[PDB]
Image 1 (cartoon, each protein chain N blue to C red):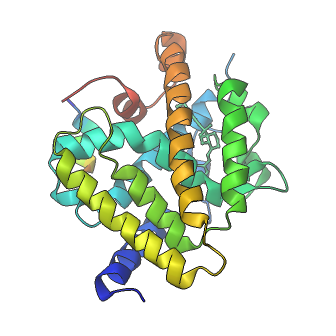
Image 2: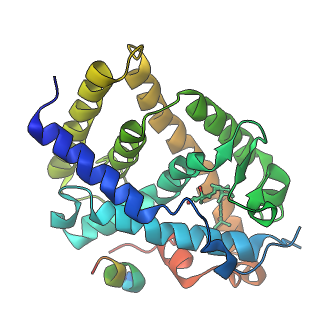
Length: 10
Length: 239
Ligand SMILES: C=C1/C(=C\C=C2/CCC[C@@]3(C)[C@H]2CC[C@]3(C)C#CC#CC(C)(C)O)C[C@@H](O)C[C@@H]1O
């Protein structure tokens, strides 16, 4: 559900 | 005396901060420019979105944060982001100007600027009183970094699952901070408690900011000025 966050968290 | 492991936590936290806080503020010129209707919303939205990315980078270098589940990492970040930003912003705050000075005069933000972005004095009054009192604490860099890390690793946030692990992370950081102040901060007998108090103020600042964010986000003419990262991190979705 948290797309950008998941990406930013590698 | 401080242990080898305690000082390692300190080192890796200081390093993490120096990697994610650019005292030159030369990245700010990339934001949508300030306008001084909500004229400051575009620039400050970009300021906040930029800062979230830095906070995620700091978090990823806190010992143990990366070993949490992604859900807890997200939960900890969605609840604590605005607090870490208020904390880290003390580094640009100035008692002289009672404002945040980030290099040039176009990147100096006083209270009136922040109202032109949709926030009221019921947020800005306690915030600026928080910034001056925290600035007065004259924190060492080691202490500033420990407080940000402690604030982030708080188990009493909506959504965290592995409460026990996060509380233990936070306990270790507190022991490091208590020891550090004791050994290395002369005249700091009451400093630890004053810092723990600031964590309590941060929660009240958080709530007020969330309140005012909602009225911004429920007005599409305003919410459209936000960034995708801001809308996601401050949005009310759950994983
Ligand atoms: C941010 C940082 C800095 C300044 C912090 C400031 C000054 C501008 C207004 C801000 C941002 C405030 C922190 C909280 C507040 C009052 C807010 C807000 C909001 C909002 C929305 C509209 C998104 O709801 C400068 C440097 O020290 C880097 C640091 O990272």
